[PDB]
Structure formats: C-alpha cells, structure tokens
Amino acid sequence: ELRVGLEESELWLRFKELTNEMIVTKNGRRMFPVLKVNVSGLDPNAMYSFLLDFVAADNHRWKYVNGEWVPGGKPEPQAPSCVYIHPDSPNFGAHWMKAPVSFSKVKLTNKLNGGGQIMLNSLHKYEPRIHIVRVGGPQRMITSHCFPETQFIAVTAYQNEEITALKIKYNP
C-alpha cells in the first residue's frame, strides 16, 4: 500500500494553530515552511511524477480584523490552481523514497506569469495537495493526498506578527 506522510508536522502545527500565512508576490515567493513529504510503498523500479496544487479550502475572502482572521459573506466559485511539477520528475520510485520529497522551489504568485510560478488569490485560504502519478507504464495511476496541517491564507504581507516571528525563528 502507498503511504504518504508529512515531514516536520510538529512545526507546521505551530503555524496552523496561529492561522498560517504565505506571501505571494508578482514574481513569486517560495514557501516557508517547505512542504516535505515522506513516501513509501512505491514500486522502486516504476516511474512517477510528483505534482503539487493548492485547493481553495472555502469560497470566501478572508480579512484580518482586530487581531483575528474572519471570513467574508460574499462567496464566489474559486478553484482550481495550476499544478506544479516537482523538478525531480519523472523519476523512479527508489528516488522518491530515499529522502523526503521537498517542494522547496515552488513559487507562489498573485499575477499570471510566464510559467513555473503558481498563481493564488490573495486573502483566500488554501490546502496543499499532492498527486503521485505513475507514468510511462501500461497502467497509469494517480494517488492524491491533501495536507490539512499545511493550510494557509495567501497574503501580500504578513498580518499576524506571531506568524512573522515564527517564520524568522525557524528559518535559516
């Protein structure tokens, strides 16, 4: 059976209890923390690609109002975000299982851009999700997995200073 776990969930949970925020820019901003996934149960000799997208967790716009995030009252249809392909793709299962798969190069933006960058809507809440695609073989297959621990609100600048502090405290 294919198993997908979140690496460093302890740390993500610290961000989630504060309501996590991720910066978007016109040119694209990398995430902190980085999504790192532990995978086991792949066929070591089969070929896979690792894909990442961001599900809009609700249809609302969020606002930081007097020290707390609150959702608006005018929902709109949202999804889907584009998909980011992990740069190691395509690769053998053994490659993906030898170390946590780390999405350290995805860039979050708020502008339609030349490619690579993933456009999100500022002030919307998102749930990262991966797709593990078995490629090249006879039987294509997709296994998907979301990571509720890694939910965040996309922002152009940090609103909650407790998030700002945690981001610095645990980055290098």
Image (spheres, helix red, strand yellow):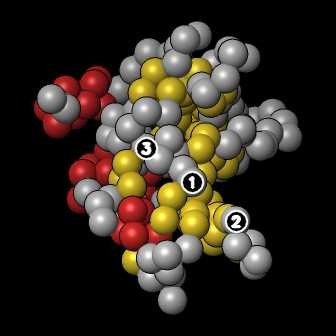
Kind of residue at badge 2: Gly
Q: Residues within 10 Å of mark 3 (few under 14, many from 20)?
A: many
Q: Secondary structure at mark 3?
A: loop
Q: Is residue 19 above or below residue 101?
A: above
In front here: 91 or 144? 91
Q: Is residue 159 above or below residue 10?
A: above
Q: Which residue does the image show at 43% across and 33% down from the upper left?
A: 105
Eye-nearest disc, 2 or 3: 2
Q: Which residue does the image show at 37% across and 48% down from the upper left?
A: 102
Kind of residue at badge 1: Pro
Outermost residue on the right side: it is: 77
Q: Distance of mark 1 from mark 3, alpha carbons?
A: 14 Å
The residue wearing badge 1 is 90
Query: Toward which corner of the image does residue 167 lie, by quadrant?
Result: top left
Q: Residues within 10 Å of mark 2 (few under 14, many from 20)?
A: few
Q: Quadrant of the C terminus?
A: top left
Q: Is residue 143 above or below residue 121?
A: below
Q: Secondary structure at mark 2?
A: loop
In front here: 108 or 38? 38
**Nearer the N terminus, badge 1 or badge 2?**
1
**CB contact under 8 Å: marks 1 and 2:** yes
Q: Position of residue 98 (x, y in %)?
A: 30, 66
Q: Position of residue 51 (x, y in %)?
A: 60, 51
Kind of residue at badge 3: Phe
Q: Is residue 94 left or right of residue 148?
A: left
Q: Distance of mark 1 from mark 2, alpha carbons?
A: 9 Å
**Nearer the N terminus, badge 2 or badge 3?**
3
The residue wearing badge 3 is 103
The residue wearing badge 2 is 136
